[PDB]
Image (cartoon, coloured by chain):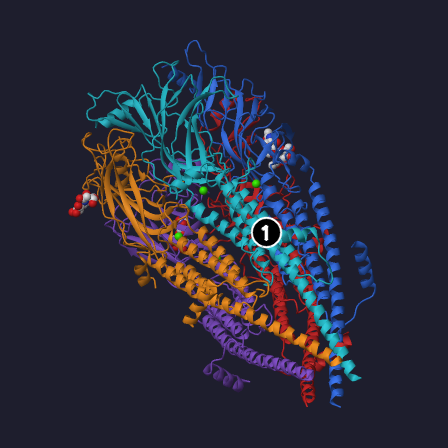
Chain colours: A red, B blue, C cyan, D orange, E purple
Amino acid sequence: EFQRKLYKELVKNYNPLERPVANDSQPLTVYFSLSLLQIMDVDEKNQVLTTNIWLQMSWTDHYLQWNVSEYPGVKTVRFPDGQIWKPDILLYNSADERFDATFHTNVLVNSSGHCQYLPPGIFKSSCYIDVRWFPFDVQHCKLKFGSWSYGGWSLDLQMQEADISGYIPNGEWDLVGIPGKRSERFYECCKEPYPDVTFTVTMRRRTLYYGLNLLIPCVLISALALLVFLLPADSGEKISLGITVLLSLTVFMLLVAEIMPATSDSVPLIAQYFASTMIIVGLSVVVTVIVLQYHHHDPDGGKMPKWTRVILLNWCAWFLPDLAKILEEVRYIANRFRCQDESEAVCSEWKFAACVVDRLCLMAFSVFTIICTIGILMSAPNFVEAVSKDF
Amino acid sequence: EFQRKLYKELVKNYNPLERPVANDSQPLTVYFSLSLLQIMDVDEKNQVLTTNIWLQMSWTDHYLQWNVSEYPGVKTVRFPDGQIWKPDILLYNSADERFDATFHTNVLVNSSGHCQYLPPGIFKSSCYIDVRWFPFDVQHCKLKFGSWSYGGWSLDLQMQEADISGYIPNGEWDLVGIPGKRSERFYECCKEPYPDVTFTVTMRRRTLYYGLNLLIPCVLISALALLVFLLPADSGEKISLGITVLLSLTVFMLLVAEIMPATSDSVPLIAQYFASTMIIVGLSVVVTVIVLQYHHHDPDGGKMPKWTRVILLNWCAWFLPDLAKILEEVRYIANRFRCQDESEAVCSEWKFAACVVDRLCLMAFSVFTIICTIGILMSAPNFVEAVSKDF
Amino acid sequence: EFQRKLYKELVKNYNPLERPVANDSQPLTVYFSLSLLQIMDVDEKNQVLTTNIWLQMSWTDHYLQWNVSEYPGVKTVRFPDGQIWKPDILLYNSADERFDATFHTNVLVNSSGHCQYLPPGIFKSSCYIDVRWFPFDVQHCKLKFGSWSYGGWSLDLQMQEADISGYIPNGEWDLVGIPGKRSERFYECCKEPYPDVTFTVTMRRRTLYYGLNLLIPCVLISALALLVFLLPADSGEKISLGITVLLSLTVFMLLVAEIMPATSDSVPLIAQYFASTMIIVGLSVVVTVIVLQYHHHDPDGGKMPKWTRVILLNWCAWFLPDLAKILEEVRYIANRFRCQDESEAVCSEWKFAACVVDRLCLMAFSVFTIICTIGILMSAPNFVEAVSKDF
Amino acid sequence: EFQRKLYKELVKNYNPLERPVANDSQPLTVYFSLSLLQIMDVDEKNQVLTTNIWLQMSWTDHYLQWNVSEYPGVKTVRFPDGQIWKPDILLYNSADERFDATFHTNVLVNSSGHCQYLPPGIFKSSCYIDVRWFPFDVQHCKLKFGSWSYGGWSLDLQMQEADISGYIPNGEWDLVGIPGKRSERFYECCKEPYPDVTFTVTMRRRTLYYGLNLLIPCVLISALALLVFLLPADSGEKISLGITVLLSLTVFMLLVAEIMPATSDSVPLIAQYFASTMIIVGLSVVVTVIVLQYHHHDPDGGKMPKWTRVILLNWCAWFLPDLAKILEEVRYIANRFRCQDESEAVCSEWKFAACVVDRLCLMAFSVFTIICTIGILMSAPNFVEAVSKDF
Amino acid sequence: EFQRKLYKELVKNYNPLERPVANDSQPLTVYFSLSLLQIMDVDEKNQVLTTNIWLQMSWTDHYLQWNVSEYPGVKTVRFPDGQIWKPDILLYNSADERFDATFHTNVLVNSSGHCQYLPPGIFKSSCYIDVRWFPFDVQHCKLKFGSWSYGGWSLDLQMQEADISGYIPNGEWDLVGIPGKRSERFYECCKEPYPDVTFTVTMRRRTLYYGLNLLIPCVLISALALLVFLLPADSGEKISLGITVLLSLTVFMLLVAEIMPATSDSVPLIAQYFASTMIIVGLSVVVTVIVLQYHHHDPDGGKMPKWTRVILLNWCAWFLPDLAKILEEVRYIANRFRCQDESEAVCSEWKFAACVVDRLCLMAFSVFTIICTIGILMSAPNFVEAVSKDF
Ligand SMILES: *[C@@H]1O[C@H](CO)[C@@H](O[C@@H]2O[C@H](CO)[C@@H](O)[C@H](O)[C@H]2NC(C)=O)[C@H](O)[C@H]1NC(C)=O
Ligand SMILES: *[C@@H]1O[C@H](CO)[C@@H](O[C@@H]2O[C@H](CO)[C@@H](O)[C@H](O)[C@H]2NC(C)=O)[C@H](O)[C@H]1NC(C)=O
Ligand SMILES: *[C@@H]1O[C@H](CO)[C@@H](O[C@@H]2O[C@H](CO)[C@@H](O)[C@H](O)[C@H]2NC(C)=O)[C@H](O)[C@H]1NC(C)=O
Ligand SMILES: [Ca+2]
Ligand SMILES: [Ca+2]
Ligand SMILES: [Ca+2]
Ligand SMILES: [Ca+2]
Ligand SMILES: [Ca+2]
């Protein structure tokens, strides 16, 4: 009975289009804050960040002042979108295709004339994502808020501390904080200045999934490709293994390339690792070809180099009537056998050379693989941190 | 003729913006309920739940009271969205990009002044999905409803029992119930408190599809990889089989990783199983390399260890003129043959050692595989339940 | 000149919110029909049906009655959405995220007061799809229409026969008919009853695509895997073939699982077929291992079982001075040769055993494959029908 | 100053809901045309066509007539959507989920009372796509326009020639023309007739991409699978090659099936080609098995057929004291050698038979492949055309 | 207090529908500019460009002129969408499905009557993308702006220089500039002319990602396929390697075809490279078949060509009582041995021929591969530029 009379009274001569103030040349103060319920999702490929937040706008209005004595028991009044005045605050860097995801909600007012506006939102923003240290990476995403048609001479934004109290953990990221900052900028459009409020979300990725799904299989594959050397040449399965491994590695590179963005600013870590692995395996294939070349060789058809063989041997050693016709034919067959034996002995020497080559290159490749893996993974700053918590 | 007159009369001096009550300081009561037609879908990857429900809001209005004697035969009247007052009840935890999926429908009123509002909706909600026990998993999804600009001093929500009578079975989940709960919370925004109504859907996954599509092939693949040992070394297909199996297993891991979320909170069961399988197969490859190492070996080039061979043998046994020239040459060839025979015998000893190694490691790996499979699958609490119904 | 005057006259004292009738307590009659232009699409995975239809609502209005003599030459008048009264008829079981796809169009009226409303629509509906007999399957999809805030005491729905005259063939389904049915239900919300109109679309899938793309390759793959037996053990390609076939079959199972829903209500046919095929091929691999076990075997190292060999043989047969030194050495070498020959003969016996095993298991597996394929495909009721038309 | 007065004057007593005419019983004439800027896209799978066009509606209005002498210098006036009357012309066969993609724009008027309305649009339409001759295919897509609530007695549509002057080439299709046609139809809804305007777009696909990406690899794969015959049986790589080729072909069939619709109306060309290729390769595998069967064969274990061998040979030929003990033992070993030689000779005969089988079946399969490829590709009507322009 | 009075005064007799000018026949001037914040994304497949920009419209209005002395301290006033007049400027070539992505914002005015309108937007445009030189490619995308219902006689567009000051680098493209141009066109719709403003964005792709992900593996694969020749025929892994490589190359072609559009206008570079690689590898397979044909060959079964062998040899050379019975049998066995030796020697000659063929074709294919790679990659104009910056 009093609420109705008050509602009649307030909009007697109102006009939403005016900035409500006692002095027309004195700027108005608006307190702007953010509240962050959830980190909905992150997309590296498209470079977008989806978040669920509540804005918080507060400002005092002169006209909507009423006395509590004449109107009893009524403390708070509400007004919808178009009936009163609201600041047209919205996101500068959006990717929503509608550009304003705010669900227009009510406005609360109390006798002094204060006014609150907490519009929720599922906001999409255009971060700049970097993968120089993927998966051991930390990301900085800035949300930039400000007014559009109102400037410093006519509006004045002041920042309050954000709110992470209701924050719900995501399960794929860790939140340090969302520090805020105010600035005044000078756009090449207009005379008067324009302020802005920037909140810088810091996130750290939890690496258990990407550590138990990518890295461990990669190291195991490298181990398997190292294990090829020991397989003796007699078994014909010496090179099918390596080629199958390379095909598997190619599949793996497809997988990882799908889940990463195409940024040419800086080369990523995981790409360095994959490149090293493929080069190592290719050199393994080449060495294996050399080995099978030495192993199969006709002693009578060819000969042997000197310097190579002697150096190889040194390195290995340090590391490790009618009766007359009868006689004639028997002599012949025995000589045949002796020649065969000598040929076989030379072949055996060839084979020993092949085995020593195998062993030497095996040790070399094991050392190279171990060193490269360790160095590449140590290169990441956050590694020491990420392994202490996630594991 | 009377309907028209009533409609004229009721909106003579109405204003939608007022909370309709006899006493302005006395709070209003609103009865809120839910009805659940269908569980539209669930998405583990994005962690979202899509449901089809009918809200149920009921409250009494003082102004829309009319006498039935003067207006005859008219019992119920209807009012659209903006003409009368409605509570702005909406979902707190939404993922719709429009944030309010409710299809604004009519409002029904009867002479006492009671009012009903049943707006339907395809609601999306941000559950927290867990896969610690996938596929034998049970999920708890909470839907949180409440008002936005109205508090306890001005509105009072009371909960009625939900409705699963019209529920349509999904074919991929089982519904236990949707218990509801009321609470009062204190947000770091405002002085007065705010209530909320939370419904906790419990779902259990039916495992026939995921049991006949994933687990059975995995066990069969492990069996095939066990069957490699028995393949004798003479056939060159001893290691191509295992490597092909590993490539297939990698493909399988791709498949499963696509259909699972990237949560680092806790390691999942199926990942434990896959890790065990890949480690087992890798050790199988290594053992096979060792076997082919022993089998192919030059007796004259090398020798044999003692402790290893004797222990191996024990374990196996418990488990299982010119005429003179003629004579000279004949003597020579016979001695050659005897030496060849001795070499062959030593080679045979090597081969027997290889076979016994094969058998021993085969039994060891069979035991390990069986034990690990059984233990990993027993680890799931719900297993005993899920196998009784689904199968 | 007369149209304008009529339009002025009709809305002189109108109000869209009243149910237009002579008697306020007498219910109104509404004739509701459907017309079906196209079956836009079907999605098994999400269980949705997308259709293009035209509603048909007809009802008489008392107020919009005018005399044709005073207003000459004007027969039909039109009214847009909010100016007159329309029944809020909409789909009960929708999946559109907007929940009302109807494109609000005009309303036609003629002097007696009759009114037509044909709003088009691309409607999405939540069918219950079943794949127990895929691809030889028939589907029943129900569209449920009714009013929301109007009941029997205040509205009365009557059904007319649907319209398939304009129906456009799809190319992937066949339409039998869309029988309609009326019912009155009692929802656990309200006192008065509520009617509903349900149209049951029946569809049959045309199988040429899925018969020439899935089944034929499957049978050919089974044939190829049968052809492995005949490959003699000497060629080392006896088991690579089968394993490659199994990998291909796994790929095929991936393909089919992608295009099918995850319903645990009932096991599907195609899954039965695939399971049978994989089990058959696995037993083939095992048999091949056994064969290569017998073929490669040292006669001197081991011996032979009796019962197995004799039974195998029976089944096959039914189915199919210095001179003294010279003499000594010659004697020795000849004895050596004789022993070698005997060993070779025993080896030949082993090999013959392997070949007979091959043949027997080949026939067994051919019989099993043929019988299972024929039985599984006959199991489908619609098969006899689907092969008469589609092929 | 005059524009304002004119705008006041015109809407003094207007009502958008009336059909504007001098005579109420005389029908109105509307000139309807289309203009086609771009062929946005085509989707075979869903059977949809996305286009960018400008409608062109023209009609004369009686009320908006003004004298140019009293109002000077003002020639054209503009009116937005709801202020004046417009015909509710829209697409009959749409797939947009909003059903009317027209961007409501202004309306232009000139003193005589003529009125223009050119609303742009990105229209989606439900073509009927056919792939009987893919990729050498020509497509007919019909766009059907007409009014909804206005008939012949009240509206009269007349068609003007379309406009392809601004047409922008797509790069994946070629446009012949868009002939238009008018018709009057009799829907089973209503008494009065209803006209319609149908434009029939004709498109021809440019085949360079699909000719250099699909066909050429297919023919090369068939060539490689032909090249298997020449590989001699001694090299164990005779059947791995063919099976790998078959796996590749399966992958290719997956690729092509993804990019084609599931229409069972008629079998497509590319499917015929793939079926022929797979059957050819399967018979190749079978022949290879036969060859390896003959090549490996124990002469003593078995014998040889007569008719087959003789016919094969003909076709090939047309196409292409103590001393006594010493003597005894020597006799024995020599007889042994002679028997071995005879066995080897019989084996050689077997091998020659295998080689001749290889050659004969090779020529047969080459002839079959060439003939089938040529015939299948000639079968397409448009082939001769498509190869003259695209290449 | 003055703002309110001014707002009352200005809209006393306003009408948004009039073009505001002193003279009704004199055209109005509008200054149009663009500002470019970000290049959101590019899609080659669908041929679309997504950008984030700010329009800039400026024009003077006669009615909204007020004196600053009477109204003190108020300099700028604001007006929302429908209250005042705005030019309906929008994109001609759009792909948004809503066709106008502009977020309608306020309008700023100052006493002289000047008016600004800066509506932001995430605009989608239909470029024409070309891949003739992918990845070393430069793209020209034109954005075409203009008015719809207003012409030269009634509106006059003038262009200001664009703004790239706030431009944010993308990380996948480089921006040269966005030159603008004005034109007057004559559409086949209307009498009066219509202007337009076209901005031509130039972009250059940064190639590090596509250079380290595609090209390097391709060259390594070609190297591996070259390395097959050196593998001696004795090892049975001579052709499995090449076929596995071809399968990998097919997978790679799938990958690249997915990420490229299906434009038949002109053949692309990367396709030329892939075609060359596959042809080279196929000829490699054929050569390998020839080699294995010569290597395995029965000397007694056949003979040798003359011209081929002699030319091959020249090119290689330039490049690089009872006792009588005893005697009889001994004679026999010795003759047997001699014949065997001669056969073996002829076989050795065959094998040497095979090896020389291997070497010659190896050098030929290495030369061909090197030349083709170098020539194909040099063919790109931008290559020399792109390698200087990106690397
Ligand atoms: C109306 O709302 C304002 C906004 O909070 C209230 O003003 C606050 O009052 C408390 C009480 O001492 C102060 O601590 C705060 O500093 C005040 N706000 C600000 C921004 O300074 C006010 O009390 C409310 N009630 C009335 C009747 O005005
Ligand atoms: C108003 O618009 C109409 C529509 O075009 C104009 O009428 C055309 O005038 C030309 C000039 O001779 C004729 O060739 C056309 O045939 C006319 N249109 C039609 C549909 O017949 C008219 O000139 C314009 N101006 C005025 C003042 O009416
Ligand atoms: C209102 O806005 C106009 C638009 O800029 C202002 O006019 C500009 O004034 C400066 C000052 O000398 C000139 O350099 C510009 O050339 C003017 N604009 C144009 C388009 O020529 C004007 O000063 C503003 N204030 C008032 C009171 O009119
Ligand atoms: Ca992510
Ligand atoms: Ca699921
Ligand atoms: Ca389907
Ligand atoms: Ca296409
Ligand atoms: Ca791109």
Tell me the residue that label 1 is attached to: C318
Tally the numbered discs: 1
Quarter of the image where the N terminus of chain C is located: top left
Q: Nearer the viewer, residue E139 or C45?
A: C45
Q: Is mark 1 within 8 Å of ligand 6?
A: no
User: Seen in the image, is E270 located left or right of residue D122?
Assistant: right
Residue found at x 30% / y 51%: D202
Q: Is residue B52 above or below residue D162?
A: above
Residue E288 in view: yes
Residue found at x 71% / y 44%: B374
User: Seen in the image, is A324 located left or right of residue E245?
Assistant: right
Q: Is residue B77 above or below residue C204?
A: above
Task: Determine the image quadrant of residue A378.
Answer: bottom right
> Mark 1, chain letter?
C
Q: Position of residue D95 (x, y in %)?
A: 38, 41
Task: Determine the image quadrant of residue E79.
Answer: top left
Residue A16 in view: no
User: Seen in the image, is B301 located left or right of residue B63?
Assistant: right
Q: Nearer the viewer, residue D100 or D194?
A: D194
Q: Is residue E162 above or below residue E337?
A: above
Task: Determine the image quadrant of residue E298.
Answer: bottom right
Quarter of the image where the C terminus of chain C is located: top left
Q: Nearer the viewer, residue B180 or C126?
A: C126
Query: Which image quarter has ligand 6?
Result: top left
Q: Position of residue E387 (x, y in %)?
A: 51, 69
Q: Nearer the viewer, residue C284 or D309?
A: D309
What crowding class fits label 1: few (fewer than 14 Cα within 10 Å), some (14-19), or many (20 or more)? few
Q: Amino acid at mark 1?
A: Trp
User: Seen in the image, is D168 located left or right of residue B185?
Assistant: left
Q: Position of residue E364 (x, y in %)?
A: 49, 77
Q: Position of residue C22 (x, y in %)?
A: 34, 15
